[PDB]
């Protein structure tokens, strides 16, 4: 039937924990149990808007929704999540997460995150498999997945001792990975027991938050993590300490948490072997200006090349790139067509080459306060005068 | 020098050639906001440069160039892009091109009086932000208002007063 | 593009054709109320769109078109309805229609000087509210002042700033 | 409709025909005192009618029409009475009359420069109060300022706002 | 940053939109009650905060909007509800909503002088109690005078000095 | 000397550049608290210094720059940081930077009246404590009220009268 | 490609011969081959005997200057081929003329060669 | 095959030094080592317009390319250059720069720049 009038309903709600909206789509892949509550097929991705669609598509105690509630606490982002089926052995549970073209025609596992585009208009710019990233087989395939999407794949080290994850972050010279070692302990609604969340979805939720108002060019290191208590392993940062757990994990290209109860992240550098691609802004701006160059020049990717086609878009690729210099994303740039790689035979088959040469803002890793207590201001001071 | 005048003209808007209906253009009158200045110890004021003023670049067409009417009053100001091409043939043959890339707000569509036996002349105006004139492919003017770019002949004439405002 | 000009013209008022006496029309000059804006960190102001201004659409007839004199200064403002038709024939034959539906106040009847041997030319003016121009049946301009409708080429350019004022 | 223009003209003042010397008339420019109005929740102002403004009806003669000079600056303002007749012949023969009864103050006698070999052209002006235009004997305008009569085509357009001021 | 200015405005009272007649809003001038403080051991006084002073939030209409006149001087002070919406459109498209929820006492209905041919301009004034400002939905101001809430950007600036007053 | 005037302006708050919206800065009026002093044995009073008085340093924006509105009336007085940069270009080329570091209390956020079609002009006012002015990097002013620092051109003008107050 | 059935993506046609690979070339070739047909039907119903090849070819170039006007081609040239052996041989039969036109190539694979530099880092910070 | 749709590439561009398209014609004779990359026989002349022809006709490990970069850093001209094959003896290196008409219908060294006429209607105006 229906109810006319007004209806007060004695419910059980709580903790309005709203976040400012984001736009950077992340991918997601973890285990869930498809009973009768979860209305989601276990190998295809579904688009998630907020906590309502995260709890409708997946179970409440499912490891998907425990990771989906880790990002919506921090940023009202757009989740492309393909769940996987729970398995028994860690070998077969890993191979369900990677998967591939193992069906007759379709894709399963992590490989269904390319299908975020063409179902959802949502290309995943971040990749996170929470808990299933301490194994070598998934994290090898997450980086090959993140190279195709041109994204940032978030991992985590094992929850073992400190020297184990240093030995685990040597298998990658991958220049698009990002590893967060200490496992975040979260409260979860009057438990009086701290659940060891993998801290890959929280750090992937920090990137969508800092994408919104600080910009993609902003270093996503110093900023807050919400919904977090005292983590699995206490990673201090002591200044002037040769063997402190932060600097032992910063030199191994691993993000950590430093302050009380995991307030904030600490990684500014990605899991790379090149020193040109060290920071997580030199690889993030490298990708997230070139979707903004494209979104704005999607008309230019098919049009009749006339006499003025090379010139009117190279004055349009500049004319967008000044807006990035306007909002502080880059410093002075130069964008221009190649004189030496534009012939008529290349134009006849459609091909035409441009150069884009910008430089990125360097993040302020390591301020340095070199200070002496002098005996200087003592003479003219402290006298009768 | 050779006697060199304007002969022919062209207009592009977002790549679309107006090869058939442009009777007139108008490049934006670049003028310095001159504040005349007579102080103690002189006479006959000396006209310190304060900066430019607004740059309306009128033109007109006399057909139903709906591809030029779609850019009036959009939400994105400085989304009207367009060049004001034009060749100066001189006397000794080869013509010297002058192009002028624009980026501004189409702030005026002025349809003429329709006297039923005369032309139409949809007179327009764009209060441009970005402005780049070329002569024979060589640069003369980069006028970008925001983020402080006044580059006369390639050398930036506001760069000394941009690394002190901290822009 | 083809050379395309105005050839012939027509005017309707509440359906009544003025097929015999309209020597001139004037579509309303659509102009943005440009407020030139130079602030800290720039020069050469950048002309933010503030909105349009008033849209008078003059025309004239030279007979005793009493069916056009009845709409002056009525109690219902925006009760003068009328279209400003006009065809642009081009060069390749088929003509491109331009019609312009109006809805405003006939705020001026200006009878000319009667020099007894010349024409009459009752010059008029309508400060229109509603304004819809079409080209070949395709939409370009919906300008409705009240209830916030500025729809350039069918897409509403004030819809983002109408669901925040709560209109 | 038929092509219809002004051909001939006449002027009466207190019954006296000016059948011999009127080179020009001017009917009063009826214009609404438009106050452009942009408020919260709109743009592109909508031009509310506030009323008319003053109605000077110039004309000129070039003889010693002392019967027109006697009405300048009398003690009784609105004692200059007169009609501005005029016929529009059209194309199909029969002419459509336009007469315009006036009642105002002859506020200006402007004798022209007497260049001794040209015309005289005593240009006049009457700031009329009462104003009644007819077309083919049918009423279009009753404009009486005092006692609130604006009757467009016979129906009173201020009668709804005259039985509330209690006039 | 991009240049960003006010273009359009709105006002609600009790949910009723004033989409037609608000020519001028005015947000209340937020001002710290400054006492210039010079004491022993210093000069050039340092202006310690003492709290705010009262916040008149004037606005106007120019019709007899009876939905607004009934809120003058009720027995229920702080019963005038109302939001002062506004949209700042910027240059790069998107319009930023600025709203301002009020709850106060409409203390002054000021009709202007009625010069019979101009606007009426009913200038109003509410001496607000509650005042919540938003920018694009994100919170900036809450001023609740009674029971002591001053939340600048979400953090209560009186919370450190309200748990020692025992409130 | 060469003629030297202001051309461009900038403002930082907490490192955030206001490169888009500051139409008007105002450096704080430095003023000696003058008491006109006439005593026995003289006339025509001689105006002994008593120290400065308070230094409001107004400025304005005309968007809702929320990075500036959050500094109004915090519990932490003297937490508004900010530099008032400016460049005086002269006539012979080189531009002389004039910066002015502040540290004060943002005491007055004054939105103007919103007339729906003009600028918004959020006029602000900080009642500064710390004030350091530079000219081309070279030091001219330090005004630290608390703990007594007044350094004109690098030499502390209170240092002779602070080692006898025992500070 | 995208979210819904937004855009197409094919620029090629199913031709092994890579000359007529683009669909915009075959649709202009099959459009100008229709102007030859209507240029022959118009040059057969009015007794165009001695001036046939001049009536067809100039009437063909009335269509080619239209395509240069509309932007459909860039080059247009109707050529008298040098495979005309003898005057009695060519005027009696087999006059061989050509039609060349450079169609507007659609922008397939634009290429952005992108950098991250250390050049303008010195100018900004100092 | 080919590729459809836009492509972004991690690449290396070395700090653009574009100049003016000059009109005078420059002759040049210097020494290099021929390889499979340098697509030019030694004693034949070839006109060059941009650095793409000084990297494809001649190797980047050369000494023409040291001098074609010298012109193209300064003014974009038309250089008609020949190659002298690499010798070791300090007279025999210079004696191959001079050469003569030892070939049947070809001049070898500096004399091969006399073939600028009747080949492009562009004689060298400078000799380097």
Image: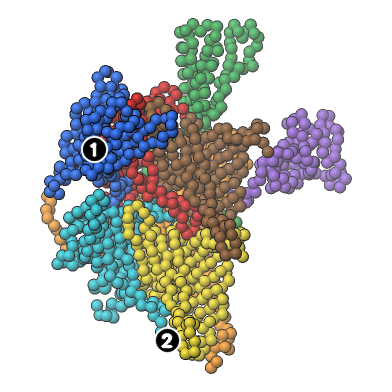
Chain colours: A orange, B brown, C red, D blue, E cyan, F yellow, G green, H purple
| Marks 2 & 1 on one chain | no
Q: Nearer the viewer, residue B125 or A66?
A: B125
Q: Is residue H56 above or below residue A172?
A: above
Q: Is residue A236 toward the left or the right of residue D123 in the image?
A: right
Residue drawn at the location 61% of the way across and 52% of the way down: B155
Q: Is residue F165 above or below residue F21?
A: below
> Which numbered marker is on residue A287?
none
Pointer 1 chain = D
Residue drawn at the location 16% of the way across and 66% of the way down: E76
Identify the residue position indicated by label 2 in the image. E40
Q: Quadrant of the N terminus of chain F?
A: bottom right
Q: Quadrant of residue H82?
A: top right
Quick check: can you spot residue A339?
Answer: yes
Q: Nearer the viewer, residue G30 or B124?
A: B124
Residue drawn at the location 22% of the way across and 30% of the way down: D15
Q: Quadrant of residue D84?
A: top left
In percent of width and height, residue E14 lies at: 20, 58
Q: Quadrant of residue D148?
A: top left
Identify the residue position indicated by label 1 in the image. D80
> For the view shown, which residue lies furthest in the bottom direction?
A384
């Amino acid at each position: 039937s229906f109810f006319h009038g007004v209806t007060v309903t004695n419910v059980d709600i709580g903790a309005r924990t709203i976040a400012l909206p984001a736009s950077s789509v992340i991918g997601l892949c973890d285990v869930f149990t498809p009973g009768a509550q979860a209305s989601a097929k276990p190998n295809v991705p579904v688009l998630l808007t907020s906590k309502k669609d995260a709890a409708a598509a997946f179970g409440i105690g499912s490891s998907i929704y425990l990771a989906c509630e880790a990002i919506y606490n921090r940023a009202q982002a757009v989740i492309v999540a393909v769940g996987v089926e729970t398995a028994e052995t860690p070998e077969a549970q890993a191979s369900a997460v990677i998967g591939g073209i193992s069906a007759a025609g379709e894709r399963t596992g992590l490989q269904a995150l390319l299908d975020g585009k063409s179902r959802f208009n949502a290309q995943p710019r971040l990749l996170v498999a929470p808990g299933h990233s301490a194994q070598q087989a998934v994290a090898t395939a997450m980086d090959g997945l993140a190279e195709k999407l041109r994204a940032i794949a978030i991992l985590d080290g094992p929850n073992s001792t400190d020297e184990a994850a240093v030995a685990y972050a040597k298998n990658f010279g991958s220049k698009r990975l990002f590893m967060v070692d200490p496992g975040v302990q979260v409260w979860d609604s009057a438990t009086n027991a701290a659940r060891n969340a993998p801290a890959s979805a929280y750090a992937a939720g920090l990137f969508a938050w800092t994408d919104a108002e600080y910009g993609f060019w902003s270093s996503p290191s110093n900023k807050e993590i919400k919904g977090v208590t005292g983590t699995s392993r206490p990673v201090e940062f002591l200044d002037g300490d040769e063997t402190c757990r932060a600097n032992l994990l910063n030199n191994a290209n691993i993000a950590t948490i430093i302050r009380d109860d995991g307030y904030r992240l600490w990684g500014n550098r990605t899991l790379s072997s090149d020193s040109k691609w060290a920071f997580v802004t030199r690889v993030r701006t490298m990708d997230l200006v070139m979707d903004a160059i494209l979104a704005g020049h999607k008309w230019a990717v098919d049009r009749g090349i006339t006499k003025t086609y090379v010139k009117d878009v190279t004055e349009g690729l500049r004319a967008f790139m000044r807006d990035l210099k306007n909002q502080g994303a880059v410093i002075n740039f130069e964008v221009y067509a190649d004189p030496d790689l534009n012939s008529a035979s290349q134009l006849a088959q459609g091909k035409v080459y441009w150069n884009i040469r910008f430089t990125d803002v360097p993040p302020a890793e390591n301020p340095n306060f070199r200070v002496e207590v002098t005996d200087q201001w003592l003479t003219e001071v402290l006298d009768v005068a | 020098m050779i006697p060199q005048t304007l002969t022919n003209t062209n207009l592009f808007i977002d790549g679309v050639s107006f090869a058939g209906d442009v009777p007139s253009l108008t490049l934006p009158k670049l003028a310095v906001k001159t504040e005349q200045y007579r102080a103690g110890g002189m006479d006959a004021p000396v006209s310190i440069d304060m900066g430019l003023e607004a740059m309306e670049a009128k033109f007109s067409t006399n057909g139903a160039r709906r591809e030029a009417l779609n850019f009036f009053g959009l939400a994105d100001q400085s989304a009207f892009n367009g060049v004001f091409r034009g060749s100066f043939k001189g006397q000794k043959g080869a013509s010297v091109p002058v192009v002028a890339t624009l980026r501004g707000l189409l702030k005026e569509v002025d349809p003429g009086d329709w006297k039923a036996g005369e032309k139409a002349e949809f007179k327009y105006a764009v209060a441009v932000s970005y402005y780049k004139l070329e002569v024979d492919g060589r640069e003369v003017y980069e006028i970008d208002p925001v983020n402080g770019v006044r580059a006369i002949n390639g050398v930036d004439q506001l760069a000394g007063m941009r690394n002190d405002l901290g822009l």
